[PDB]
Image (cartoon, rainbow over all chains, first blue to last red):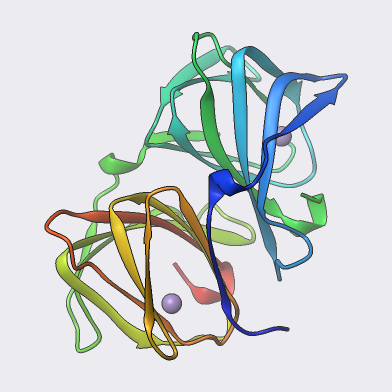
Length: 118
Length: 114
Ligand SMILES: [Mn+2]
Ligand SMILES: [Mn+2]
């Protein structure tokens, strides 16, 4: 593949609205996308106040790092809120979702193997 | 599912001929991860990761402070809120020229170890 290094302010990427049957009040920035990533992609998600990523699962893992705010994590059984400075590992096929119960934006980094897209 | 405060992971001090004033936390390691690992590095004031390369990429996010990134030639400082993509085989390293600790998240494919 190519050489070099990219160094960029994440906020220089516009936050794009995610709207699907199971996601509302969420925006995403693709930081290191399919066009460049050899193995895995880096996204920055913004959950607006009251935003929801419904419980779901997929046949790849998630690696998450919470950057800002209080993120409510939905589990197969119940939920738990974590804050900036927490990491999350979600196994392949594990049920998970997210909610923002606060009045400010919540941000988290989310990385997946590139076979799951960007 | 694992949910944990990164700070609570015990950092490992690194002090070698090429790395000094650096601590490393393995957040999501080989034990858990099927494809890539998540580390958090803390660079003390004056700390240094000297120029090196490896056959895998880095994906980095700067969490705190002003990080000096060493390039094959020259260097570039970036701040909290920057991401960095280092291509496989690219010469790189890091320095902290400030008076406070710098933190960055760093992910590599699992062939890189943890
Ligand atoms: Mn998911
Ligand atoms: Mn390296």
